Length: 49
Length: 49
Image 1 (cartoon, each protein chain N blue to C red):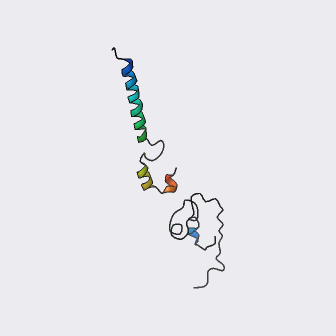
Image 2: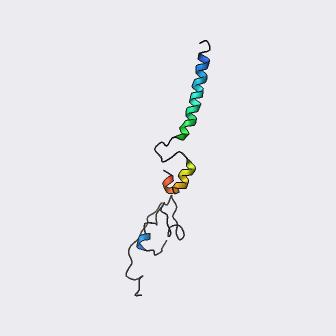
Image 3: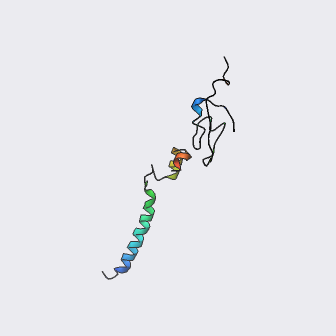
């Protein structure tokens, strides 16, 4: 999967975590057997204005 | 003092049943002994423990 979220919502992408970005947009199961990969991208996805 | 053994057996069975019933009112280290209250007060990820 591939999506772009903010910094304070990266912790919500995890099995068991709940909130706003993890309950209405993208929900992970409690038995999720995988690896979450995220990194800062404040160089091409943020224009002036 | 004649019907002693039968009375003792009946009392032992009654005490065993009463203890088995009262064991449902213990926390065993949890926050409470009410499954509904636990599920209502905590989200499933935390209430699973």
